[PDB]
């Protein structure tokens, strides 16, 4: 080669996503007392989430 | 006897005595045999002439019509679900902050 060129290029990368939290009783029962008292003889499927 | 329950005015009803309306409080309510829990406040969601209640996208009741005084009300949950507790170790101290 006898001459050259300067080239500027672009690269795009994800770094992070959104952070969420879920309330187990409010999603399942929803301020019911008949429910959320039946959802107490089920196991620990709400701390593990 | 064959009966149906759907979004329309009630014709024949059971022998239960009505009571007073309590607003802006967490109460159980029974409107025309439709039971629920929550806070009753006034609203503006104008209904159809026959419509008794209206649901939302999650298929949960959102607004209801008072049977005796034909006035719309709406229902919001009793639970606030965005509270977080900043604490040092419970060993060191028993003080917290709330967000
Ligand atoms: C290596 O390549 C570069 C281009 O990357 C050459 O630079 C270019 O030189 C030419 C001739 O001098 C310039 O043309 C001029 O254009 C202006 C109008 O823009 C005009 O008024 C002048 O009379 C002339 O025609 C050209 O623009 C210039 N390019 C850049 C970016 O500067 C360079 O000469 C090459 N070198 C070798 C060793 O071949
Ligand atoms: C449904 O009834 C309420 C209360 O009825 C009143 O008491 C009954 C025993 C009987 O005497 C009715 O004729 C009475 O109206 C009605 O609410 C009343 O509305 C009137 C205006 O028409 C008002 O002056 C009264 O103060 C209201 N009373 C109360 C306690 O709110 C209501 O209008 C009736 N619903 C219908 C079908 O419109
Ligand atoms: C709790 O506090 C005591 C008394 O200051 C200290 O001796 C102990 O190491 C602490 N334990 C923990 C788990 O922080």
Image: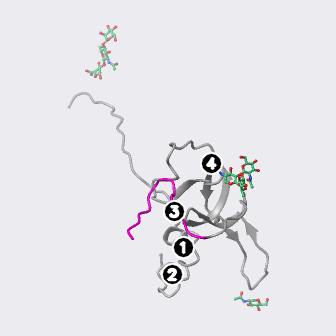
Relative to the observer, which residue lies in front, B8 or A41?
B8
Check if mark 3 and mark 4 are on a common chain: yes
Q: Write the start and end of the magenta stretch as one range.
A: B1-15
Q: Do labels 1 and 4 touch, CB within 8 Å?
A: no
Pointer 2 and pointer 1: residues touching (CB < 8 Å)? yes
Residue occupying image coordinates x 62% and y 43%: B44
**Marks 3 & 1, CB-CB < 8 Å contact:** no
Distance, label 4 to label 2, CA atoms, is: 37 Å
Q: Is mark 4 within 8 Å of ligand 2?
A: yes
The secondary structure type at the circle numbered 4 is: loop
Seen from the viewer's position, the closer of residues B78 and B39 is B39
Question: Which element is circle 3 on?
Answer: loop
Seen as rendered, the residue at the extreme left is: A1
Whether tag 2 and tag 3 are in contact, CB under 8 A, the answer is: no
Disc 3 or disc 4, which is closer to the eye? 3
Q: What residue is shown at x 51% (from left), y 83% (from top)?
A: A38
Chain letter for mark 4: B
* Image position, residue B36 (x, y; %): 58, 66
Q: Separation of disc 2 and disc 3 at Cα?
A: 36 Å
Q: Nearer the viewer, residue A33 or B12?
A: B12
Classify mark 2 as within 8 Å of ligand 3 or not, answering yes or no: no
Where is residue B15 drawn, in percent x and y?
60, 70
Q: Which mark is residue A39?
A: 2
The quadrant in which the C terminus of chain B is found is bottom right
Check disc 4 and report the residue beneath it. B70
Distance from label 1 to label 4 (Cα)? 34 Å
Residue carrying label 1: A25
**10 Å neighbourhood of mark 4: few (<14), some, or many (≥20)?**
few
The overriding secondary structure of the stretch rendered in magenta is loop
Label 1 environment density (alpha carbons within 10 Å; few <14, some 14–19, many ≥20):
some
Check if residue B7 falls in the magenta segment. Answer: yes
Residue labelled with disc 3: B12
């Amino acid at each position: 080669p006898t001459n050259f060129t300067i080239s500027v290029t672009t690269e795009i990368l994800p770094v992070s996503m959104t952070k969420t939290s879920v309330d187990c009783t409010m999603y399942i029962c929803g301020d019911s007392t008949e429910c959320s008292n039946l959802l107490l003889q089920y196991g620990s499927f709400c701390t593990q989430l | 006897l064959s009966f149906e329950l759907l979004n329309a005015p009630a014709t024949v009803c059971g022998p239960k005595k009505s009571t007073n309306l309590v607003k802006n409080k967490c109460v159980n309510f029974n409107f025309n045999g439709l039971t629920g829990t929550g806070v009753l406040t006034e609203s503006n969601k104008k209904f159809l002439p026959f419509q008794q209640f209206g649901r939302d996208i999650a298929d949960t009741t959102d607004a209801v019509r008072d049977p005796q005084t034909l006035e719309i009300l709406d229902i919001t949950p009793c639970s606030f679900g965005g509270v977080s507790v900043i604490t040092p170790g419970t060993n060191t101290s028993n003080q917290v902050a709330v967000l």
